[PDB]
Amino acid sequence: SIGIIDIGSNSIRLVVYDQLSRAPRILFNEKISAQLGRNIGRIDEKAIELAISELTRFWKLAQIMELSSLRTVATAAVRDAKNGAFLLGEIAKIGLEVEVLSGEEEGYASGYGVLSAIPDADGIVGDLGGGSLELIRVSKGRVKDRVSLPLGVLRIADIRALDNFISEAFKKIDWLADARDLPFYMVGGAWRSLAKLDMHVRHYPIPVLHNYIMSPDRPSKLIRVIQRNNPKKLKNKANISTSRVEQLSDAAALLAVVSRHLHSRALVTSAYGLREGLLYLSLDKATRKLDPLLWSANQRGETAGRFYQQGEALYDWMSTLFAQDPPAYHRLRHAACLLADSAWQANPDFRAEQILSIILHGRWVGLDAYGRALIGQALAVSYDGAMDKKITNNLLSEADTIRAVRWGKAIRLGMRLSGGVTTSLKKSTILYRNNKIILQFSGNYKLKGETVLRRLRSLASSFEASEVVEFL
Ligand SMILES: [Mg+2]
Ligand SMILES: [Mg+2]
Image (cartoon, rainbow, N blue to C red; front, side, top):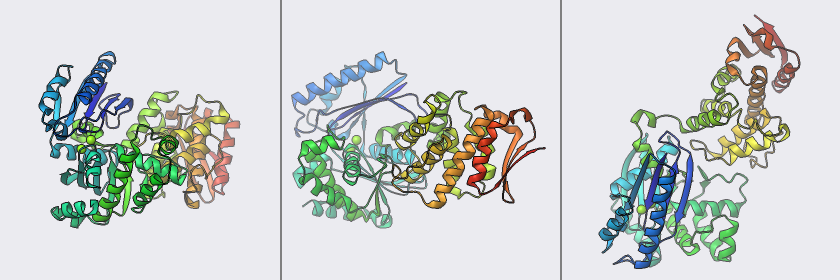
């Protein structure tokens, strides 16, 4: 239902989202490699010709998709070309009014994009685009400070000396000194592509874009990877075809110098950038505070489940076993319960495989790799799978491996007992007391049956407990 066209100096992108919601699904995403800024200074005719044809396609797609809103933004970089104002008028005649973003508006959108995907972010956001580097301090749910620098990807080759430029620029930014030893949240296409390169180079058994973590030493090592490889093979094998390898080398150099000068403790990818920041700021303010993992997992069980979303009564029912879970884990148990019906159409013996890829390889935010592994292994267990551990890179502690097995067995007992109509679990309680796992019925006694209690035996076994069924 909504579209954003993001015009930069090094590429243009259309993204269509299913609705304006807390965590919307991407229906369509197309990046164009026209480089409006390369000829600064004047934008060259052939760039303009490429851009107007592509933008006209973006307009036409918006018409046939019947979008409820299409927003077009451009950077000040493009506007301030000698002929920038003329190009903006040529775009308007397509039917696309261009909203030119100041440095302030650009940095605020990129920073709230990271806060949308990572609500607890506390660090510096770096948006490396074609024409600018935006640096944004985020803390406490807010953008706190911001600077816009002329260090886009196109500008890096002209300098790269790179250390001295950053050193000089950084001296004038007085808030960097209070922001040391914090994460560096990377957004923009070049740095997201560099993280995909790192995943490939490292063979990291969970290739998650969102919240992928890199040491501050990785960028310097990636420069050497690019130099030590055939550029064509590297791009294709790492799934970053369309990236310009020379630009990626420049991006890595900049990342190394910026990270060192900011004293970044970790480099963290955000799947949400400027475009998702615009959406977040378009929300009602109270909607912004909703948890985007649980929002997105709720929507998935609504659209995929047999009886829409029944995970709420399931989470309520199973959580009396899990009251002592660490504070951060309750929302992960909840997200697993919301997704507990999402592989029902698969043949029984492959549902564990499916649900695991949905969790590990879905576009979830508000979650790190360890959390994906926890939810994914709980849900694999819920669908009668063993736990590979090598697909999850042995990330999990033994305590949390036991915890995931217990979550998964409780989920599947609840799902099998209720048939998936989890409202009926409102008349039941499942408890761990005195070395017993006790399924209590205060009502819906007819659900008990006999065979389904094999799931209770399994759960009891994972607790080293006596299976008990009690009617109250
Ligand atoms: Mg940008
Ligand atoms: Mg920019």
